[PDB]
Amino acid sequence: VQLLLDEPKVKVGEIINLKIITEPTSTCRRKQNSTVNFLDIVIFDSKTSKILPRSNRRILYNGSLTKPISTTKVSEINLEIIPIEKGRYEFSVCISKSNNQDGIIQFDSENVILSVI
Amino acid sequence: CKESTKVLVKQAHNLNLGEYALELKSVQSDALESLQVEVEVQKNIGNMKNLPVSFSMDEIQARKRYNTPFENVRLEYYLLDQITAFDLIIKTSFTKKNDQGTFGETKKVRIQCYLQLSVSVEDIFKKDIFFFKFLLNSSVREEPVILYSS
């Protein structure tokens, strides 16, 4: 996974497409069953302690963040991080394979940070 | 008298297409319950009924809980009220009568029309800028809703 972003230095009242790019692997050959695989996008404060789904007065977005990918090819995804009253955020993902709890199988470490003035 | 109380096949006719009939449905309405009939006919189709075939009249009309049968009306909007239910029934009859044959029908449809996409709001308000944040939810439990504009 890489994370392609527009700017790291946006002001408050502005709308940003975020673009993750995922690369499914040769070693997906163990399963093939759920071709669909559910990710998440989690937002960290760049101190600790991630914001909730109800990111009230911090970050805004379009739709539920679960936003599936294929185990086929280089799928893309998006959100619209409509920022509000912040500084120094962080974005990272995880992979969950399903919807249930204990479906989560890996946690990537790609942590693109952006600042808000 | 045939006296066939049981032990047979009962009814042997089919509601096929390519014939002038009636069709009552509901679409595109803003939080106030209605219905919409459709008449796919030609050459002066006659009047039709729209009864209230309920047990205790929960699917009520506005002032007097009426049936209010139409007359040469194809598509309309029966703006009802709701006297505490989530299911209904509707016996609908239509004297078609194309040419030298008193064509009639009686369809007892069972439309239930509670809302699905239950939507709540929240504003936030900064200095000379302003944002809403809309909650979107399905009023039924574990029957899913797709959604493709807002």
Image (cartoon, grey):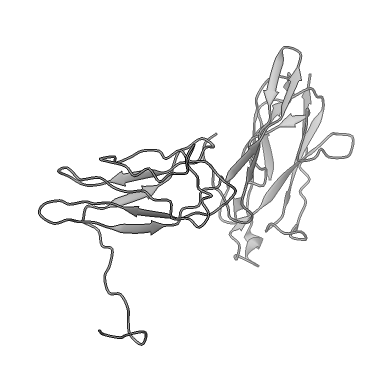
As drawn, the residue found furthest toward the bottom would be B7
As drawn, the residue found furthest toward the left would be B100
Q: At 27% from the left edge and 41% from the top edge, which residue is drawn?
A: B71
Image check: A92 left or right of B73? right
Q: State the residue in front, A60 or B12.
A: B12
Residue B47 in the image: x percent, y percent?
25, 45
Residue B127 versus residue A36 in the image, above or below: above
Residue B94 in the image: x percent, y percent?
27, 51
Residue B19, by quadrant, is: bottom left
Q: At 70% from the left edge and 15% from the top edge, which residue is drawn?
A: B129
Image check: B42 left or right of B118? left
Q: Quadrant of the C terminus of chain A?
A: top right
Residue B77, by quadrant, is: top left
Residue B38, by quadrant, is: top left
Residue B97 in the image: x percent, y percent?
17, 52
Q: At 43% from the left edge and 51% from the top edge, which residue is drawn?
A: B52
Q: State the residue in front, A59 or A109.
A: A59
Residue B64 versus residue A72 in the image, above or below: above
Q: At 63% from the left edge and 38% from the top edge, which residue is drawn?
A: B119
As drawn, the residue found furthest toward the front would be B64
Figure label count: 0
Residue A94 in the image: x percent, y percent?
74, 49
On the question of residue B119 being in view, the answer is yes
On the question of residue A77 being in view, the answer is no
Residue A8 versus residue B22 in the image, above or below: above
Residue A107 versus residue A90 in the image, above or below: below
As drawn, the residue found furthest toward the right would be A47
